[PDB]
Length: 118
Length: 118
Length: 118
Ligand SMILES: O=c1ccn([C@H]2C[C@H](O)[C@@H](COP(=O)(O)OP(=O)(O)O)O2)c(=O)[nH]1
Ligand SMILES: O=c1ccn([C@H]2C[C@H](O)[C@@H](COP(=O)(O)OP(=O)(O)O)O2)c(=O)[nH]1
Ligand SMILES: O=c1ccn([C@H]2C[C@H](O)[C@@H](COP(=O)(O)OP(=O)(O)O)O2)c(=O)[nH]1
Ligand SMILES: [Sr+2]
Ligand SMILES: [Sr+2]
Ligand SMILES: [Sr+2]
Image 1 (cartoon, each protein chain N blue to C red):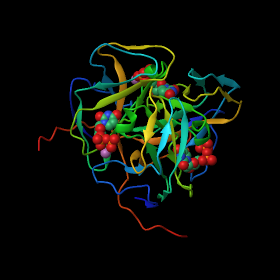
Image 2 (cartoon, chains in turn yellow, green, red):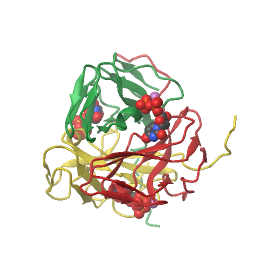
Image 3 (spheres, chains in turn orange, green, blue):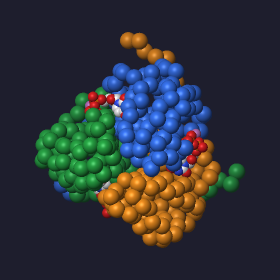
Image 4 (cartoon, rainbow over the protein chains, first blue to last red):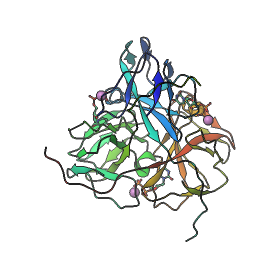
């Protein structure tokens, strides 16, 4: 479950894990560079959930790597996508195209317990 | 829960998170290249679940990076493993060896809610 | 839920997905190198759970990549963090600073089912 706003996120099919995120403008990412691509997307998830921004098969096969990608439940800004080209060729993203996906997960990172020495 | 077929996936121990995926043939991956390694593995997961193909500690320590890796519930093909060498040395994979693992997760990417302006 | 020990893990806020892991000593990571950074952190998670060591936004934006990162339920050692610099500049980590985060997830990688030919 989640709420979201923005024009750079597209409605998904039920059988896909994630929503596609769409590139805002044409941009070239030279070999070995890192670019921070802005989106207008903002999400609200339920307690103990988080958003995970990760790669698509079509851009991963060209060497685009999405790094970072953990969207905490308390974040109220716009998602930024951190992209590094680890391929051997310049990558050109075209306005509009899918270039990452957002998956919503639940974590259990809470309720610390006593260590069992057993 | 899942169903699977193929000879390149190995049965796992209960206390490990993922199934090992096995390299189909000897292959060298030069510094900075990307190779798409085919498996014969096919999986069926329950609704709102997905498979996650990600790295092993022994190959990550040599600079092998598994990229992409999100196996949607609707996919009915064979898993492909997208590998990039981000290390400083050529990597040689040997026929049979483990080189990635498949973990089954549930996502909550569905049931869009109204935004709370609160 | 989890138990943990060690001085290189910090208590978290409820609204963040993961615990920060803290660098043990000053260390420089040259462009394209890979370093294995030791922690003293040990965790115990419940059955069918795993720990996921992954990146922070502030270090991902400089080109630090955390690779591997899957901490199995049966592991009883100290977490090691595998770091590769995929940026274009040398990265300097300072003693004490956050440089990765640990998120606790549940997997469903178990209870193999019959394939449905339907
Ligand atoms: O790829 C990413 C990773 C993080 N964030 C946002 C959401 C996340 O909750 C916030 C974390 O920022 P921080 O707490 O200031 O940084 P750090 O992760 O370095 O602790 O940044 C993004 O938009 N994109
Ligand atoms: O590392 C990967 C990533 C994806 N896939 C398969 C499963 C996934 O469901 C499908 C997605 O292909 P697509 O929808 O055509 O591409 P995209 O992810 O670029 O939208 O590719 C793999 O086999 N290996
Ligand atoms: O980034 C990582 C990845 C793994 N591990 C630890 C926990 C994990 O359970 C164990 C796996 O070691 P292995 O079974 O010997 O290696 P492999 O993953 O190559 O099968 O290594 C770490 O400390 N850091
Ligand atoms: Sr798709
Ligand atoms: Sr193992
Ligand atoms: Sr933070």
